[PDB]
Amino acid sequence: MNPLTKVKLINELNEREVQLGVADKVSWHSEYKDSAWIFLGGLPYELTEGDIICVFSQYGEIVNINLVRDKKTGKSKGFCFLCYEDQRSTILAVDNFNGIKIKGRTIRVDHVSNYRAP
Amino acid sequence: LIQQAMAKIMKANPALYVLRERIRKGLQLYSSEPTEPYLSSQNYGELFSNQIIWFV
Amino acid sequence: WEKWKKLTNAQRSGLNQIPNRRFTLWWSPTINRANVYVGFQVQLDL
Amino acid sequence: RQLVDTTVELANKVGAAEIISRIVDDLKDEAEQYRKMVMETIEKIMGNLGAADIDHKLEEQLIDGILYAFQEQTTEDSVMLNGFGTVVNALGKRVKPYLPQICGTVLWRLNNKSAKVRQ
Amino acid sequence: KAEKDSERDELYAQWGKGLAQSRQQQQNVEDAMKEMQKPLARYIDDEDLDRMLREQEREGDPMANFIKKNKAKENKNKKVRPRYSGPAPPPNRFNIWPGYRWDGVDRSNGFEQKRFARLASKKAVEELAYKWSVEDM
Amino acid sequence: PFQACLKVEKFGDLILKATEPQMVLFNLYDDWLKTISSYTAFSRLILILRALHVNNDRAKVILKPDKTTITEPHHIWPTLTDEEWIKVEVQLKDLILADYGKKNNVNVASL
Amino acid sequence: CAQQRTYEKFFGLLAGRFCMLKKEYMESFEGIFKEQYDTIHRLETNKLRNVAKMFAHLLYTDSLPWSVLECIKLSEETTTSSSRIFVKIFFQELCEYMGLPKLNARLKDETLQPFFEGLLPRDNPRNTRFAINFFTSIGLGGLTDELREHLKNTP
């Protein structure tokens, strides 16, 4: 199961709950109302913080940024953890940015349940 | 005895039920609310009926 | 209030009597009030 | 479906009462698809195992959740119908003290304004 | 030791309860206290509401120029962190203003907009369905 | 809990500041009877009184929902539209069940 | 009158018939303008507009005395923005009914100077300036200029 299917499935989750007519309170996001952390994955290896922030700031102020790069060479592994300032912005970002193409690579977004600092 | 027996016959009786439902079917009236509100053999869905009643 | 076939001459004509009959029932305590007088009653069959 | 299956298996090992007592309070949840997940398991479980271990407080919460879930169906689906059917025909003769609530609710929903609920 | 990591992880714990909703809760509790120390019924003479309605700046009026002047004069003198400034951001269901380093481009997937469309459409279909029910009646 | 009315400043102040034994007459269903039955209006009143008895403070808070909620001089209670009356009815029942949970050590999602 | 969706002269003419039958309605309507203006800030702009039109109609039918304009002490401070929109709608309306000429004659006849005082305020130059500029922005440039002629020659 390659990450593009993990994109397709989150999008399926959204549009399926749309077909079912779920109220905004029992959305599948409601299980995450205590965490303002999203995970971005699939990122290209040349994007830096400056880019991740200039892209993802569309939906709020970004409080924390954590781009996980391989310790030996320092180069990005290709995924990030991002702490918005209001949980609701994470709602917005997961719905809106999951599946956008940045430089051909189609990045993917999803919340984080019990983030552990590094 | 007769007070209580008659107050209960008016709520329960099957033939009175058949009547009320022939009336409803003839008017084609339908309720909108489910659950039949907190009416039960509690007294109040009776109490505000035409007989005046005071709470003190 | 209460949100093909091959049919005869009379069924594609003539009024529909059901809604007339239902209007009369609903207002029947007024339409059939006792004390407006001709002094003759009629008792229905059974 | 995969979650439904392994929950029924865990039921087979640890007995019904445990699983049931874990998920009865969800028959009163807001997401219908979720209520229907828990109804599908509860129904499959009690169909297999039978309700010998359902205690009093559990059969109480169970009949209550059953009724509520029945009274909220936005959809068209036989899930809650078979849930009711099997749960009731498994409780067997322990369901006497509830037939007045059941009968009263069914007569009252028979008089409602929309043909989905009357049907 | 425990003290240093306590500092670190308590900070991270608020940041995961991210600040904005926390300060909103703060103003909520103080609003509830202010209120609870007041009568049950609010009239139209209550000084708070009278004053608020005075300062309520509605359209058209040429006082607006002088008053926007007053407040844009004063609130210039603030230690605020920067706010976004540029071509209007798209609309989002919570009305959240972009961060101050958003580069303007709108990168969305087209979800907020189709949501808005879905809601307007349900309104239209409700009018149609009412009309048809009663038309038959 | 009809005595909970003694918290509503109108009745309370009237009684406190009376100099004479005297009979007064109020209407507790301000206008509701234009568009609900006496049945629904009694139910709504019972909720309001119960919640004003049980906590009285978060009850004031719920019954003044918006900053521009107001009450008119001959009225006991705020002027809300039937939508907001439905909402605040729900919130008062939640208040009452919460305080029953607190002071009887029950999970209320179980009843 | 005020709660309706849009104006029609019915309510104005009806009150007019009552005040034209006896005085008490004339009294109560001068009081009415007083208090309505003072507490207008509470009206959403449609009802505010309808009140403004109502008073314009009464004034040009001369059921109210033109004195009642005493109330608009048209400083900048002494007036909320809502009061300002009320004066805007009111004066637009009066001008569109009696025309700028008859409106000008009315506002320029002498005996109504005391009541038109704060409306044409020359004592304090600051509100004199602001008044003039407001009146211009809405488009009563004629009364505007006459007063500026006065003020420019005053210093």
Image: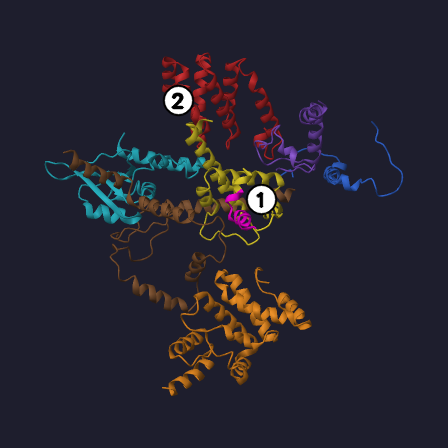
Chain colours: A cyan, B purple, C blue, D red, E brown, F yellow, G orange
Instruction: Give the vertical position of A90 relative to D20 (above or below).
Output: below
User: Taking the image as drawn, is residue A82 in sight?
Assistant: yes
Q: In screen coordinates, is G90 left or right of E83?
A: right
Q: Residue at x 50, y 52 (%)?
A: F70
Q: Secondary structure at mark 1?
A: helix
Instruction: Judge depth for marks 1 and 2 and give the one in front.
Output: 2
The disc at residue A98 is none
Instruction: Give the vertical position of B52 relative to D20 (above or below).
Output: below
Task: Please tell me whether the stretch drawn in magenta is mainly helix, strand or loop.
Answer: helix
Callout 2: 10 Å neighbours few (<14), some, many (20+)? few
Q: Secondary structure at mark 2?
A: helix
Q: Position of residue E66 (x, y in %)?
A: 37, 69
**Residue named by callout 2:** D22
Identify the magenta region. Answer: F5-18
Q: Position of residue A5 (x, y in %)?
A: 30, 33
Q: In screen coordinates, is G27 left or right of C25?
A: left
Q: Position of residue D33 (x, y in %)?
A: 44, 30
Amino acid, disc 2: Arg
Q: Nearer the viewer, residue A10 or E68?
A: E68
Callout 1: 10 Å neighbours few (<14), some, many (20+)? few
Instruction: Give the vertical position of A86 relative to D22 (above or below).
Output: below
Q: CA distance from mark 1 to mark 2?
A: 43 Å
Q: Residue at x 77, y 39 (%)?
A: C29
Q: Residue G3 falls in which quadrant of the image?
A: bottom right
The disc at residue E130 is 1
- Count of all numbered marks drawn on residues in the image: 2
Q: Residue at x 43, y 60 (%)?
A: E51
Q: In screen coordinates, is C40 left or right of E33?
A: right
Which image quadrant: the N terminus of chain C? top right
Which image quadrant: the C terminus of chain C? top right
